[PDB]
Amino acid sequence: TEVFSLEWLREAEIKHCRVAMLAVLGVIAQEFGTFDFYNAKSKLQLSPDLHNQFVQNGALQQILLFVCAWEFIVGLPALIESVNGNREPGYFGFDPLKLGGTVGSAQWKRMQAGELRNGRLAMIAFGGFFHQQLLTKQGIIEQL
Amino acid sequence: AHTVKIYDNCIGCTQCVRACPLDVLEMVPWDGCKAGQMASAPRTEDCVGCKRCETACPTDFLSIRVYLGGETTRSMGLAY
Amino acid sequence: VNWLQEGEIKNGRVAMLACLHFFVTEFYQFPFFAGAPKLAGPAHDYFVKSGAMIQILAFIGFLEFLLHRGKVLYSDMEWKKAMRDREVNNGRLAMLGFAGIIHGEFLNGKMPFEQI
Amino acid sequence: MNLKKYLSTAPVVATLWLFLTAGILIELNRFFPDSLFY
Amino acid sequence: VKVVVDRDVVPTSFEKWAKPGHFSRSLAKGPKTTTWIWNLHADAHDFDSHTSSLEEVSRKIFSAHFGQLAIIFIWLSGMYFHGARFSNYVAWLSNPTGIKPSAQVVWPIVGQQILNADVGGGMQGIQITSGLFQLWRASGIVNELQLYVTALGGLGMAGLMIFAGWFHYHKAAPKLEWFQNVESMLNHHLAGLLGLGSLSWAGHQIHVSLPINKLLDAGVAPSSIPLPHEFILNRNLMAELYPSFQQGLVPFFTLNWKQYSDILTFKGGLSPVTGGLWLTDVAHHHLAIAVLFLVAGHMYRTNWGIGHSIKQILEAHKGPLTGEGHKGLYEILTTSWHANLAINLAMLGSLSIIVAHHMYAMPPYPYLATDYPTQLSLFTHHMWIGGFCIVGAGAHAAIYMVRDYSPTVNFNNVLDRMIRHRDAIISHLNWVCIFLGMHSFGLYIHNDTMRALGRAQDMFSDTAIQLQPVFAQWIQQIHTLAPGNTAVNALATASYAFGADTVTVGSKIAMMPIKLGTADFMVHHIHAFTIHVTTLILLKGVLYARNSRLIPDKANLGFRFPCDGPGRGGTCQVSAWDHVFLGLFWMYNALSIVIFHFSWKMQSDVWGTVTSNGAISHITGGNFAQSAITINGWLRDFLWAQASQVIQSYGSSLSAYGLMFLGAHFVWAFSLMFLFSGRGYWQELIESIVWAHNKLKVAPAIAPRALSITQGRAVGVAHYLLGGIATTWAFFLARIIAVG
Amino acid sequence: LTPCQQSEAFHKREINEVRTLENRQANYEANSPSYLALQSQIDQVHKRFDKYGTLLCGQDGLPHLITDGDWRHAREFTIPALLFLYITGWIGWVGRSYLKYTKETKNPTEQEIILDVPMALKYMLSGFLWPLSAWQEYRSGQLLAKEDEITVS
Ligand SMILES: CC1=C(C/C=C(\C)CCC[C@H](C)CCC[C@H](C)CCCC(C)C)C(=O)c2ccccc2C1=O
Ligand code: SF4
Ligand code: SF4
């Protein structure tokens, strides 16, 4: 209900909806050639328990977690104020935003066009996409 | 009982009788201050010496001194 | 603020000196009768017996040099712009480049990042 | 903005610096022993 | 009863965190003094010393409730983690006896790895006495995976409460009207919390008992233990382990309740397999408590018109000696957030003590009675918790007459009389304290005299037969004959401390018919002495907090004030908070003597070993049959023989309990710096150091000043308690590990 | 008092300490990984005794040392463990003193003691060569003070 709290809430939704989509378009992309084909022998070597505790990938994930830090340390102040960081994509978007508003009469609020639906669809779908494939060994009951 | 002695640092802001419990001090017209008041303690026989005027006393070194003297029924604050 | 500016600039000059300090040596220890062949060979080969004495003497002499360079900066009563504005930028560009150049050799073979 | 002012408080700065001083000493007694040369 | 919400009242901004002392304008504009640094934290929790708008005070304390609640959840979520990453709970699940408890490891940095106690189970570390392993075994937890899932599930609940205490405030906010619904509050605390809580855990230990009862008590390996869902997915498995589950909620509606007798029983006593109470009696117990709370949770006016209310209930109770009795107590508790806290701290404080007694008397957890370190630690733990809580009850029952009591608004002639004949209450308690002191401790002086004098202690033997086995002996005999006679449906006593000559042993003695004698009448009256003195000084601080004979204008000064001055012969330490400061000390003496009594008397006559060639041989075999009557035996055979288990441990892994033992006397005697000296001399001591600070200008802008007169005593009692608990904390954790 | 490499009453303590540790060492299986670290711990124990033997140490096995200034034992007092304390402590102290010099000015004195801009804390590194410069500035402190102290009356 308050300003500064819902700010981080809607931001975190946007800051992860793209992450919850490039990962889906990344996990599907890496397994597009091994989705079926005898169910990839129950995910084959892609099973996390089969991995050797990420021996070779741990030192790589540390580098990724480092660069991703400053990436979000650019996202934290670029959101602050309009100028510089957000202002240049500001008038860029305003170029399609003007045409989209012309198609949508007075203004056609883009956040109602698809800022919340995409943001929540990615989160909910990725939450269910991580449980059906990574959080169930014995099914017991058939899953449909 | 207790011996009340008033310094020459008085400003006359009446802090004594405001703080003071049983009204030992008293404001008197005086010709050598800014506000024109001076604290004076006639009823020193009834003084208890609780030393709550030195708290409200403004001056760098307090203006109302009460040196500890003898103790009687009037200065012990007892009801028996 | 101002304190970072002064440091951030002095270290930028130290950087610009460090690359040229290694450019003459590396180009001397790679081709033509080099006193140091591969980067893995002469990593810590001792020389003569004193060794540490000439090192500590070089340390003391360089320390006295910076001692005078600082004490002179105190005196003189110096002072109490676009070139300075470009220099404030390339100083930051220097400090972050000279850590990475050595980070290269710290990879043993400069290949562990890309998996194999 | 104001988060840096809260980061600049006496207790936060004190705990941060004391964490640095304590961790350096934990790593010192874990790594090389004092060589000490006469 | 109405949804009245004031959405958005305080914004979410770091602006207040930038200002040190935003909660008070007096603690913001003038931080020029060292005393301000301590005042910022002393008044940080005195929420009634900021704003008077109750709609905001209620919206600053329920926030602190959720904050403290989040701290507790962060605390509990780690306990399940420590018993999985580095511990021995699974190995202890297979072998419970030889493997000592442990759930804390040290690192090789400065040779501290000596603290790694060899407990067994392929894992070394520090022994634990928190009862975690007993609780986890009583919860059916076997695999390490069940620890991590509970911990990760605790992180979610811990985060939701932070986003709740930050919700009803910076985001939402109920009105003031939502808090006078005390009628609607007890209908949800006694039925939603107590009721559904006693029912939810009841429904758990009915389907999770057999992984502990009809499995781990038979002799199956932890790997052969089936899964908890395999018993629910197949009702016939529960049906075979209990031939009552075949029905499946069919005689529950037919009122054929006797067909549920395989899990729901009233046996009594302990089980001769686990080591504690029956796993089937507690399930029926919580079911019985749940239904009682589902009934007791419907007693006050909601928004349908039926039921009583705290209003007219108290508006109806009268009484001859009370006059206008009980009336206005509704306005007492529904207006002062403080007012609820003393009755809460009082009841809950005595509750922690009473539940501590119920711990050792009837051990409710399996493998808890034999675990002597855990049992000894838990009793005294809740013992001291309730000591602090009851003194806090006095601390705030003193707050009420000063901060929220008026001679026009809230009125009970009962509380009026407690303040009208106030000089009579304490006079009675005073004479009671003196009679219980000049005798209970007088007899200690008497007996200690009789021994050093000669043949007087010899002729005291007949009096040693008196008092002891004279009273309370018939009470135990009532409980011996209570089953069968006055308890036809009970085949055992309330606890084996009642059943005479009935001893239950599982390679180590669990409980014993505590045969009173020699000096239990002595220590129980030392207790009653230290109890009446504690109640006296705290109740004195309660009812003398408003009207005092010496100084009539008492309400003007406050609660945490030094004094008035050298007048009237000397007005010094007259605040009710000082009656709590010293009330903490007599509570300290009370709880100290009680923990001494409990701890030592246990191994004296209760705790021991068993052999077939004989019968019972205690750790310390029946010593306080004589060494308790005199003061000397309390430091000749008690405080002296304990150094052989706290100091003779540097060669082993119990060296830390000796360092903390000798170091707790340091901070305790460090309290002797503040409790004896005065601010005047120390303030003359700074200005010399400030002179040295003015010599080099190294004087801080914050002018160096001494501690406050009240803050010095608050720190003094803090050290007198911390240094006065960590010694016995190191002592209770010293012998019990060596003689375990 | 003889050195411990020749003091036969010191090596016996090493043997006795390892003997007391060995009973705790042998009760558990050495092949277990959670107790394979005990051999590394006793390696630390062994690697600790050899350095102290060089220092003169008590015949009793309680290893004593020297603070008179003897150049053979300057390592236990004078040079290392002592002078660094003085420098490191005073590198903090004179840095604090420089911060005390910049504690006045217009912005409130209380704000410049507590809520300081982090930049002053980052400048702390200035004091590489305190000694005589600090002596000058401390002279100036006593000087500009001009004997302005408390009354004490
Ligand atoms: C010592 C003492 C004081 C003075 C108490 C003081 C000065 C408390 C000192 C405590 C602080 C915390 C120590 C100073 C440490 C600074 C906060 C610096 C810390 C910086 C880093 C280490 C974090 C009294 O005011 C007093 C009053 C009445 C009776 C007895 C006494 C008494 O004995
Ligand atoms: S306290 Fe002193 S200055 Fe104040 S009114 Fe009284 S005499 Fe005047
Ligand atoms: S001595 Fe005490 S009673 Fe008399 S005026 Fe001063 S404060 Fe009041």
Image (cartoon, coloured by chain):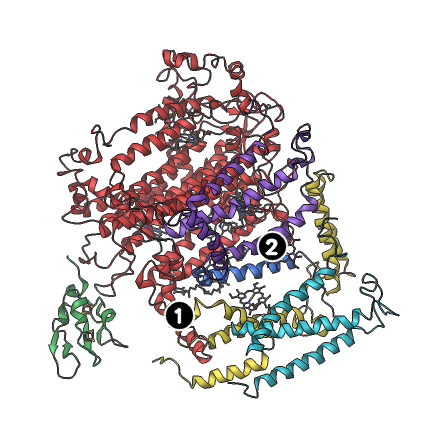
Classify 10 Å Cα crowding around label 2: few (below 14), some (14-19), many (20 and above). few
Q: Chain of mark 2?
A: A
Q: Residue furthest bottom?
A: C76
- For this view, does B35 lie left or right of residue E558? left
At label 2, the amino acid type is: Val
Asked whether residue E139 is in view, the answer is yes
Hue used for the chain lettered A? purple
At label 1, the amino acid type is: Glu
**Letter of the blue chain:** D
**Letter of the red chain:** E
- Identify whether A128 is placed above or below A82: above
User: Could you say where residue E419 lies in the image, as x and y percent from the top left?
Assistant: 18, 47
Hue used for the chain lettered C? cyan
Hue used for the chain lettered F? yellow
Q: Which residue is mark 1?
A: F110
- Identify whether E325 is placed above or below B70: above
- For this view, does B56 lie left or right of residue E381? left
Hue used for the chain lettered B? green
Asked whether residue E469 is in view, the answer is no
Q: Which residue is mark 2?
A: A67
- For this view, does E184 lie left or right of residue F74? left
User: Could you say where residue B31 lies in the image, as x and y percent from the top left?
Assistant: 13, 83
- For this view, does E611 lie left or right of residue B74? right
Residue E606, disc? none
**Residue in front for this viewpoint, A33 or E633:** A33
Secondary structure under tag 1 reads helix
- Identify whether F61 is placed above or below B14: above
